Length: 69
DNA sequence: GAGTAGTAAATTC
DNA sequence: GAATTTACTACTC
Image 1 (cartoon, rainbow, N blue to C red):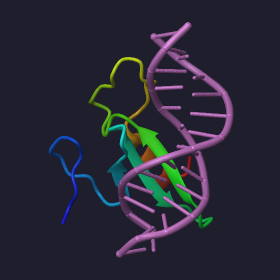
Image 2 (cartoon, protein in one colour):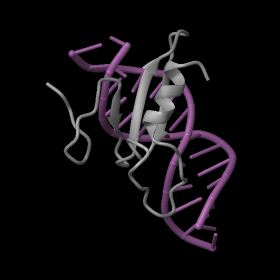
Image 3 (tube, rainbow, N blue to C red):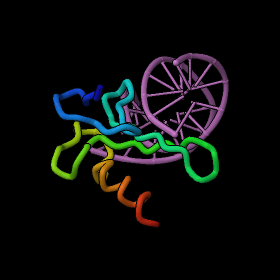
Image 4 (tube, protein in one colour):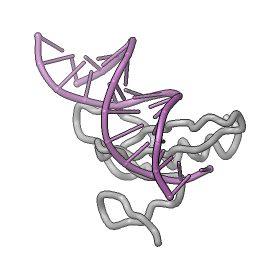
C-alpha cells in the first residue's frame, strides 16, 4: 500500500500532505520529539501559487536532514 | 515510530 | 490593507 500526493505520483513513508495541499514531512529526531518540515514543491521543478513564500523542494530539505546541515 | 487535525505566533504581496 | 505561513502538541496505529 503506497499513498500518493494530490496528483498521481508516489510519496514515501514519513512524507505526506496537510489540509492546505502543501507537503508535510514529519520525522522523529534523535531527541524523541516529532519535527515538522513544510514546503509546496515536492521536487525542485514544480511551482507555487502566487502569494506563497518561495522555498526549495521538500526533497532538498530532507537531503539536509540526511546529510548534516 | 507514522499521520491527521487543530491550533499559537509572525509574516507577506 | 487582508490574508497567510510556520511550529508542536494530542490523539491515533
